[PDB]
Image (cartoon, grey):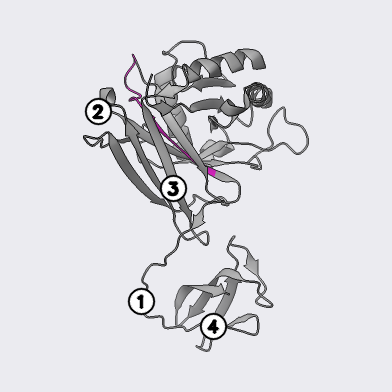
Amino acid sequence: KGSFKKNVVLEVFTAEWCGYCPGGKERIAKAIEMLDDEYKERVFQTFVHYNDGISKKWPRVGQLFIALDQTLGIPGFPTFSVCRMEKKGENLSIGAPIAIKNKIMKGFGDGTAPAEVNLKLTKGATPEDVCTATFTGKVDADLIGKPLMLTAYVLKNNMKPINPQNGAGDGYLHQHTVLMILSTDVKGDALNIAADGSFTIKKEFKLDGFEIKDTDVLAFVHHPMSNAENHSIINAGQESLDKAEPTATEQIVATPSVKAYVQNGKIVVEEEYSKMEVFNATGQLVKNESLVPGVYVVRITANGVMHFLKVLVP
C-alpha cells in the first residue's frame, strides 16, 4: 500500500436514547483488546451522536452525522465504519468482538499506507484561551495532485452523558466522543500537497463548552466524501490534548487599566471596582485565598466595563 505505518479510524454511530448502543461500544472495546498489542495503539475510535442531547448541544456533530449518512448509508444504531471503506449500502454491522476484530484487521490491510499525519498540540491555559493543533504529513508520489482532505476531531473521554444513556449500567461514561470538527466543512479541508508530498495545516480553536480534561485530537487524511467509488480514510494520527504542551506565549494586550497582583496568596486589585471574581484554570469560581500555583482568570467589573485578567500565581 505505501511508505507509511497504517492507523485505523473507526466511526461509530450512536445515541443516548439507543438501548443497544452501550452493547455496541463494549463489543468494539473487546475486539480492540483481542488485537496484537502493536495494533491496539493504532486503532482510533470515534463516536458520532445523532438525534440526542449531544447533537443538540453541539449541532455540528449532527451535521457530521448527516454527511456520513449521505456517504455510507447508516440504517440504524449502533453501527460503525472502518476507515470509511464501505460503499454506500454495505454492511455497517457491529457483530461479535471477533467479527469486529476481523473488520479492523481488514482496515489495517498490509499495515502500510500512502499517507501519514503527525500532530503537535498545545493547550490553552483557561477555558477562554485557544488550543492549537498543527498537522504535518506526507503522501506518496501516486497521491500527489489528488483531491485529498483532512478532517480533525476533538474527542472527549470519560464523559458524563447529557441525558442518561439508555441501556447503561451504573457509572457509565461516553468515550472517544466527537464534540468538535475543526474544518468549517464537516467533509474536511482541502489539503495543499507540495512537490515533495508534504503538507501542513494549523488550527487554533476554543473548546466548545466542555472541559479539557481527558480530551484527544484525531486528524485523518482521506478521499472526498463525495467520491462514491473511494471515500476512504487513508491514514490518521492522534494525540492527547489535556497532556499537550501549554501554549508558551500570551497575546499582546493593551496596556491594562487595572493592575492586579498576587500578595500573601491572594489576588489584589488597587483600582476601584464594583465586583471582583476569581476563576481557576478549569473555570470554577474560587475563593480568593491561599491560591496554589497556577493560572487564574479574574473577572473585574469596574467603570461600567467587565474586564478579564489572566493572573499567574508562581
State how far apart marks 2 and 1 are (Cα).
Answer: 45 Å
Element at badge 2?
loop
Instruction: Report the mark closest to the observer, 3 or 4.
Output: 3
The N terminus, quarter of image: top left
Residue to which mark 3 is pinned: 120
Residue 190 falls in image quadrant: top left
Say whether residue 225 is magenta. yes
Q: Relative to 280, is 90 on the left or the right?
A: left
Location of residue 261 in the rendering, given as x and y in whole percent from the top left corner: 54, 83
Residue to which mark 4 is pinned: 261
Q: Residue at x 52, y 84 (%)?
A: 273
Instruction: Report the mark closest to the observer, 3 or 1.
Output: 3
State how far apart marks 2 and 3 are (Cα).
Answer: 23 Å
Picture layout, residue 300 above or below residue 115? below
Task: Give the residue type that dot 2 points to.
Answer: Ile
Location of residue 219 in the rendering, given as x and y in whole percent from the top left corner: 43, 37
Which of pointers 4 and 1 lies earlier in the amino acid sequence? 1
Q: Magenta region: which residues?
A: 216-229
Label ID, residue 254? 1
Location of residue 65 in the rendering, given as x and y in whole percent from the top left corner: 46, 29
